[PDB]
Amino acid sequence: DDFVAKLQDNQRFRYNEVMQALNMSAALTARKTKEFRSPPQEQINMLLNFKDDKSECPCPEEIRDQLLDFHEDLMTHCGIE
Amino acid sequence: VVACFRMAPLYNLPRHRAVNLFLQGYEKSWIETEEHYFEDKLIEDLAKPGAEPPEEDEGTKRVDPLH
Image 1 (tube, rainbow over the protein chains, first blue to last red):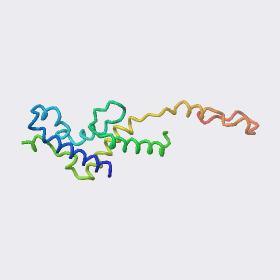
Image 2: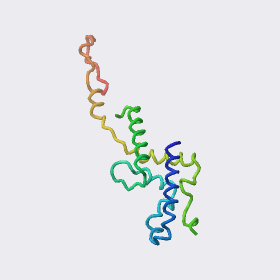
Image 3: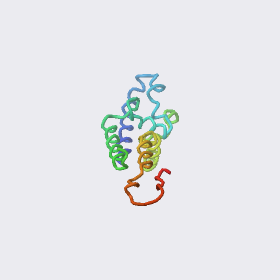
Image 4: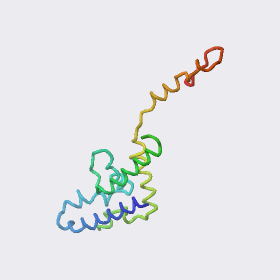
C-alpha cells in the first residue's frame, strides 16, 4: 500500500517535472518520455530494477531503501538469511 | 495527441490495480531471483546416521533418512 502510494506520487511528480522540458527538448518525447508511455506492468518492471547495481531504475534512494529494508526483513522472517 | 501517445500511467492507475501489478513484479524480479544454497548441507544432514549406532537397536543397520 504505502510503497505503491509513494511510487505513484513520485512518478506523477517526475511526469509533471518533465512536462516543462517537453517544449525544450524535441528528442525528449522519444528518449526520456518512455516510462510514462510504457505498458503498466513494464513500468513497474523498470521501477523495481534497483535490485543489484545495474541502477537504470528511475527510483529515488529513499524509495529504494524502503523496499531494500522490507526485503531483508522478509528474508529474515522466511529464514533464508 | 499527448494523451494518445501516453497510455494509462501508474500514478493514474487505481491503488489496488497498482498493488496487484507490484506484487507480480516483485515476485518475478526479487523473490524468484533470490537464491540460497542449502542442497549440500541438507543432503549431509539427511545422510548422517542420526546417532543411530548410539541408538540401541541390536540388529541390522537402520537406513538413514536419505536412504
